[PDB]
Image 1 (cartoon, helix red, strand yellow):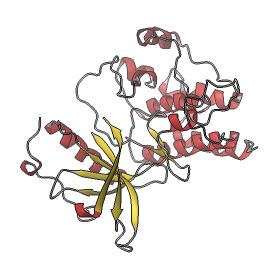
Image 2 (cartoon, rainbow, N blue to C red):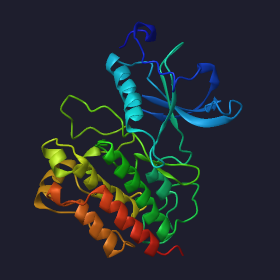
Image 3 (tube, rainbow, N blue to C red):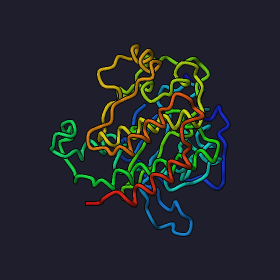
Length: 307
């Protein structure tokens, strides 16, 4: 476990520091680290009487000293990377008079995976809609536009020397205005060899988004992120589909080595599928960059129908 919060010297930053009484705790948003919904009073000094819905990150009742440094690490990392419309930005923090709170932007519509699944057409082209409360079906343009925003955010993160290392639909959140925001891009990398078998609390296997070199040699770069983006693209056009269906984790090693790739999803243009194949190129140097991906997608968004 960890020592008292007072036992440690939390990084106090006047620009982001916010009084704890200015935060009105709400319902839990995520459990891993712990996130909860909250209402901040006067986040913007220019308007101290305005309330704003935000997400509050805090450690668990059972946290290690490393967990505290990791959280701080992400906070300072977000400051470094800066702000961008397509990423979950830092809003403030509480480093005094209580536990450490890292305030970030709130995405009312949850992660992209569940977002899409809830908007699956009754048709046959997709799996059955899991959501008990279906939503309006997205247009063809909406999906490509969704890919554009994600690639847009990654392009920015790439220009900031930031390597996500786990880009996936689950790691992309949707705002109330349907804006795509990449999350968990400032997390600290573990210094202990990974367990390709470990599964997330959501029952997700990170190995399915990892590039061959990142999976076999544990090498992470912007190129490996482009690979993940290729898998993310696959998820979009499958409306929250599961990568490599019916393929065991252990089998994934051989298959990927064989140069095998996922088949084009139903209702997916060949141009968009070729983009996925280019991202899934065997040679890192041959995969396209986020800069290019943003350009092609922009061109595609303008051509793609919205009806």
